[PDB]
Amino acid sequence: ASSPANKVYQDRFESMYSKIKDPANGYFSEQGIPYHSIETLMVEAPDYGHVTTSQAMSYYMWLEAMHGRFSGDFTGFDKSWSVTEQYLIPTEKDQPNTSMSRYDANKPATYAPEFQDPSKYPSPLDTSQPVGRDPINSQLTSAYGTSMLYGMHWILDVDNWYGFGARADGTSKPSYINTFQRGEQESTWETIPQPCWDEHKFGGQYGFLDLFTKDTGTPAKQFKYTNAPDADARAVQATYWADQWAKEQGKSVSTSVGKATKMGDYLRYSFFDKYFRKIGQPSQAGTGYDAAHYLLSWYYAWGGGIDSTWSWIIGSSHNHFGYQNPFAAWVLSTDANFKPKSSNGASDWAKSLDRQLEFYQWLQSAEGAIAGGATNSWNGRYEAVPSGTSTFYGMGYVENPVYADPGSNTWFGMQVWSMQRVAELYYKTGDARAKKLLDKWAKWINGEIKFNADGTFQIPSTIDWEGQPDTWNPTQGYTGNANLHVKVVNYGTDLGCASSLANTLTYYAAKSGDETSRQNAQKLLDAMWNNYSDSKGISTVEQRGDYHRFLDQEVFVPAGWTGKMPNGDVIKSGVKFIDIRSKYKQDPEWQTMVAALQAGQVPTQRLHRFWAQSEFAVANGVYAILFPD
Ligand SMILES: OC[C@H]1O[C@@H](O[C@H]2[C@H](O)[C@@H](O)[C@H](O[C@H]3[C@H](O)[C@@H](O)[C@H](O[C@H]4[C@H](O)[C@@H](O)[C@H](O[C@H]5[C@H](O)[C@@H](O)[C@H](O[C@H]6[C@H](O)[C@@H](O)[C@H](O)O[C@@H]6CO)O[C@@H]5CO)O[C@@H]4CO)O[C@@H]3CO)O[C@@H]2CO)[C@H](O)[C@@H](O)[C@@H]1O
Ligand SMILES: OC[C@H]1O[C@@H](O[C@H]2[C@H](O)[C@@H](O)[C@H](O[C@H]3[C@H](O)[C@@H](O)[C@H](O)O[C@@H]3CO)O[C@@H]2CO)[C@H](O)[C@@H](O)[C@@H]1O
Ligand SMILES: [Ca+2]
């Protein structure tokens, strides 16, 4: 039987759940897939509001798990997994096993350098550069009996807004698409959206392939997908809770547990260097696990031929603290129900749990906030790490891992998303490493929360950094990082970030007994409910400072390359963001946005992001369960 929950906060979870599932609100598509946001004029990570992301699906899982906890009905949780497998994990028609089974574990992929400016792409493949061997493929094919990968592709054009359709048909939905392809300086405003399944039917002569990669021969028709590791790890985390809560009620979500465990098994691909180069010795091809950094890197990607049979897989050399999930790592390495079928699954996750906690500690600034991360590939070309750069297991410290436009660790959101998982681990196990990280981090953030007399509040929005952490030495541990400092540049009222912050502080307060954390958490939840509630969940008016880029951001296109988007928009040198997405001019908010830009004002919007609304719903449920009185 489930323990008693605080009725006030449980009612708030239930109300939010109803608003989110309400057909009249429009959070979901006709096929039952959650959109990034109700509003369509939306550019920030995805570039259209009605795409879905693996991030959104993992939050949909978390929300349903919590609903099962309070309603005793888990059919909604099972459906969230059913929709995920059907639409976001490439089926056998999407990643043909005829091509995947031709994968060579001794030569996973061909090397190509990464560049610091989009104008340097396409990147040339070089078969002469070393690539290490993949030690886990044989464990996976043996356990699952297929060469296909079981992980979520990160983004999906749900209603076929771009027009690529399914597997080049131009009319089916949903449509697997990708955007980012050209390095750290390619922001969301600088991409050329392309289909994951490229048969050369759209774009240029060879589809969109030769805009990004250059091979010696003529480009082959091919498919390719990219995982967002933090999303798949959150799927495991949510499923573990669904399992606990269901068992407390004599119910079962067994089939969903099996899918989550399999997902966590394939997620181990994010533990490896991009081209399987030895960690700390980037010039050398790895011989197996010496190429594993054991952290959740920015991605793992795979692809292969459509017209011929071949395939490749790559991990990622770049690591950000914001993606780590020590809670998911503890579940997969210690809980018997979540033990992966592969021979080394549970043990690799046990190594990752230890490595991740060391990574967070190495990165903790003098004040408490967590710094960026590290990379095993300097400048994305395995260049020499400049002297004086501190390192973690041979990997050089990077202030803003992967992206510089804008910096990936300048947004406060990463702090709460990632520390929330540490709070859960601490709550369940009382781990000393987790406690040490949280005591300092929570002291830092509790001094940055500002409540106003009118009931509104502000938390850090944009942050900046100075210095670097001291080189990590595992036998000596944290030095205090006196030379690494965080600076809060400005404050804001991001409701998704505040809900995640409330969740983190609630788990931490329930275990540590810290009253300040508990009352700050409750004041954040009350403030949001009482002053930011609306008919669709919660919202506030926010400035869209980068929206001028719709009209003025030039998109790089190689000299002489011309092609067309499915709707006829011409892709060629000179185009702006809006030129290859002309359908946006039909958006209901378009004229309003443009009128503001014309008058020299910053456009504003009232947004209902799926992840933010679910975050607030879950934050209320966590509080109802941990503080029942
Ligand atoms: O000999 C057999 C046949 O070989 C063929 O040649 C093949 C060759 O074998 C193969 O190895 C080669 O593979 C390369 C691919 O062609 C190439 O496209 C691929 O590019 C990677 C790229 O290296 C990587 O940087 C890029 O990362 C992006 C990612 O795409 C994007 O989704 C991700 O987005 C994240 C967001 O940034 C984040 O905010 C959000 O939250 O999550 C998103 C998801 O993680 O961002 C990252 C980083 O910016 O991914 C692309 C893949 O899309 O690299 C391969 C390895 O080098 O292909 C060759 C040609 O196909 C011969 O052609 C044939 O004749 C022979 O028979
Ligand atoms: O890529 C990380 C996640 O980003 C989420 O979007 C956030 C933007 O990255 C962030 O820039 C924005 O915050 C702005 C805010 O909109 C503006 O009013 C203020 O002046 O400046 C802030 C800082 O630039 O917030 C959004 C929403 O939290 C994506 O929603 C998410 O999918 C993605 O993982
Ligand atoms: Ca740029």
Image: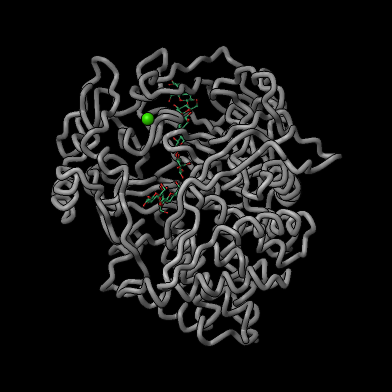
Residue 55's place in the image compared with 291, above or below, is: below
Determine if residue 269 is in view: no
Tell me where residue 260 sits by quadrant: bottom right
Is residue 3 found left or right of 224 in the rendered image? right
Q: Nearer the viewer, residue 60 or 269?
A: 60
Residue 159's place in the image compared with 388, above or below, is: below
Is residue 559 found left or right of 588 in the rendered image? right
Residue 445: horizontal and vertical position, in percent? Answer: 60, 57
Determine if residue 156 is in view: yes
Quarter of the figure that contains the C terminus:
bottom right
Residue at image x 24%, y 30%? 203
Quarter of the figure that contains the N terminus:
bottom right
Residue 450: horizontal and vertical position, in percent? Answer: 50, 63
Residue at image x 63%, y 38%? 137
Q: Nearer the viewer, residue 549 or 113?
A: 549
Residue at image x 66%, y 62%? 423
Residue 244: horizontal and vertical position, in percent? Answer: 64, 73
Residue 65's place in the image compared with 421, above or below, is: below
Residue 378: horizontal and vertical position, in percent? Answer: 59, 24
Residue at image x 17%, y 29%? 570
Q: Residue furthest right?
A: 475
Is residue 458 found left or right of 369 in the rendered image? left
Is residue 278 found left or right of 544 in the rendered image? right
Q: Nearer the viewer, residue 291 or 482?
A: 482
Residue 74's place in the image compared with 504, above or below, is: below
Q: Nearer the viewer, residue 195 or 193?
A: 193
Which color scheme did the rendering employ for the protein?
one colour
